[PDB]
Length: 73
Length: 119
Length: 155
RNA sequence: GUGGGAGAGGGUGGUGGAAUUCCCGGAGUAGCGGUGAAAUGCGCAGAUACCGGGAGGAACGCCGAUGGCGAAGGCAGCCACCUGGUCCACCCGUGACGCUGAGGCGCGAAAGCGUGGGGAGCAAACCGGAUUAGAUACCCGGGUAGUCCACGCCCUAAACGAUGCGCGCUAGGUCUCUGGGUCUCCUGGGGGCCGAAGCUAACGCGUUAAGCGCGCCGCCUGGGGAGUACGGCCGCAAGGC
Ligand SMILES: [Mg+2]
Ligand SMILES: [Mg+2]
Ligand SMILES: [Mg+2]
Ligand SMILES: [Mg+2]
Ligand SMILES: [Mg+2]
Ligand SMILES: [Mg+2]
Ligand SMILES: [Mg+2]
Ligand SMILES: [Mg+2]
Ligand SMILES: [Mg+2]
Ligand SMILES: [Mg+2]
Ligand SMILES: [Mg+2]
Ligand SMILES: [Mg+2]
Ligand SMILES: [Mg+2]
Ligand SMILES: [Mg+2]
Ligand SMILES: [Mg+2]
Ligand SMILES: [Mg+2]
Ligand SMILES: [Mg+2]
Ligand SMILES: [Mg+2]
Ligand SMILES: [Mg+2]
Ligand SMILES: [Mg+2]
Ligand SMILES: [Mg+2]
Ligand SMILES: [Mg+2]
Ligand SMILES: [Mg+2]
Ligand SMILES: [Mg+2]
Image (cartoon, rainbow over all chains, first blue to last red; front, side, top):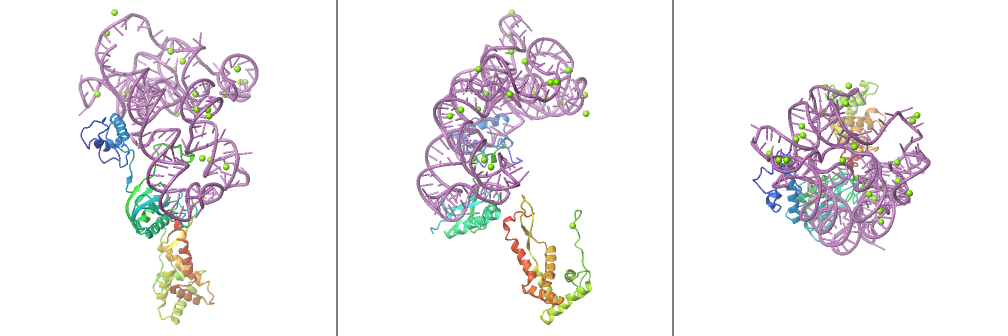
C-alpha cells in the first residue's frame, strides 16, 4: 500500500552521492538491511539509482548493513 | 543440572518436520526435541501438532535444567512453525522475544531442480 | 440440500411429559411406523426406572442422553489419494441425533428379552456412565484426539 | 568542432557480504532426511538442530521496473584503469565526402571438442530407492562428464519483433527513460499501450507501420521423400555450409 510516507518528504535536502552519511542513508533501508523500493523511498528513477550505488558503498565500508533480523513474528 | 535460567529457543521449521533447540545465553544447546524425538515417524513430523508436541518437549526438558525464559529464533518456512511459537509461549517458559532469522542467499549455489524456476 | 439450508423439522411435545426430546427418542424406537407400540415401550421403560430408581424417569432420560453425546468426531477428507480422518467439533443438532440413535442402538443389542427393559436398563446405565451406548460415544471421541495430528484440516 | 548527458556496452586487475559444502573446536542426543505414502541414504566412529573458527568454488539478494545498454549473440555486488557506441545544445568547420551491399573478413547463447587448471553447488550418463501392468520416465537418495578459469576450436538455435538496412511523407491520446528550454509546458532521442487515414485472408499493424513511396541486398515457388544422397568447401571430432 505504502500509505505511510515518502522517505524523501520525511526529511530535508541531502547529497544522495554521500556514501558516508550513515544518518540519512540508514533512513532508506527496511527493518531488514534491504534497500527500500521507490514506492516508499519517494525517489526518482535517476535518484533512486544513485542511492543504490551509495548505500552499496557504505555497506562495504561497514557503515550500512547488508541484512538485518526481523524482530517480532 | 546446571541451572541456566534464561536462554535461546531455536525453531527450525520446514515442510518436512519441525525441530526446536534450546540453548544457553550464547548458542550452546541445553536440550532439543523434534517431531521425530516424539512419537511421529514420517509424514506428520511436519504436521503442526508435531510442532507443538516437540516445542513443548523442548520446554519441559529445558525447564528441568531450571530454565524459565528464552528468546525465540525462527528459521525456515514450514507447516507448523507458529505453533511451535505458540507452544513455547504457553510452555511456561517466558517468551522474551521472537526473531525470524531464516537464511537466504544473495544468490549463491544453483538450487536443486526441486527449487528452480524462480522470478 | 444444495439450494438452502434445510429446516430443523420441529417436533410435537410429549403427551406424557410435554418434551420434544422424548418424542425424538420415541421416534428412534419406532420402526415400521408403529408409534403406539413405540410410545408404549418408552413409557414402560420410564415406569421401570421407577420400580428400580427413586428418581423421576425424565430426570434419568435427560442425564442419559447428555452422557452419550460425542463432542468430537472424525470425518474423512481426501488430500492426495489418501483420505485422512479429520477430527472436528460435533454440532449440538448431530450431537443429539447421534446420542438418541446410539441409545436405541445399544439398548437393542442388550440381552434382556423385553423391549422396555432393554431401553430402561440402557437409559439407566447411560446416566450411570456405562453401557454400550456411552461406549460408542467414547470410542468415537478417542478417534478424534488419536488424530489431532490432522486437526489442521478443520474446514 | 565546442560544451554537456544517461547507460547491467566491452576488456583487465582488485575487492565485499549472504548462502551451500567440507574441515577444526564447543555444547548436545536420537534421530535426521525424503514423500502422495514410503524406501534407498545418512547418524552412538555421535548425525540432524545450535554457537565459534577456518578452507574453497560458484553466484551476486534488496535496489530491479513498464527500467537501461549493445549490431546481434548478449550485458546488472562494489572499486579503479583501459576502451566502443550514443543523445542533446551551439549553431562553429568540410562541402554530396551519400545509401545499400554478391564474395571477403570479423563477432556470434547453450551443448560439444583439444591442452592445462579448477571443482562449493548442480547434474546427461550411470548406481540405487519408490511408482507401475511394465517404468530403460516422471518422485526420492547418490553421482561422472560438464557447468568455472585460460588458450585454441566448433557456429548452431523458437540466433524471434518468427517483421533486412536507409530516406522522405501521412491525426492524435496516454505512461515512461534520458537531454535542452522562456519548465502547470514546448522541443529532441529511446521504451510501451490505445488509436486518424490507410493496410490486412483474418488476427492484427498503425510516426518504434505490417501505411504511402524511392534505393540496394537476402529469400519463397504445393506436401512427403529430405535438410536426406552425392559432390565440394570447412572442422581434430561431433558435425557445419
Ligand atoms: Mg441434504
Ligand atoms: Mg556553420
Ligand atoms: Mg565554403
Ligand atoms: Mg554497410
Ligand atoms: Mg559460440
Ligand atoms: Mg559452453
Ligand atoms: Mg573442456
Ligand atoms: Mg579438464
Ligand atoms: Mg545431487
Ligand atoms: Mg529411477
Ligand atoms: Mg536425481
Ligand atoms: Mg540485407
Ligand atoms: Mg506516444
Ligand atoms: Mg527540463
Ligand atoms: Mg516517442
Ligand atoms: Mg518520448
Ligand atoms: Mg479503418
Ligand atoms: Mg503493400
Ligand atoms: Mg473478422
Ligand atoms: Mg495499435
Ligand atoms: Mg517435391
Ligand atoms: Mg512432388
Ligand atoms: Mg543439421
Ligand atoms: Mg577435410
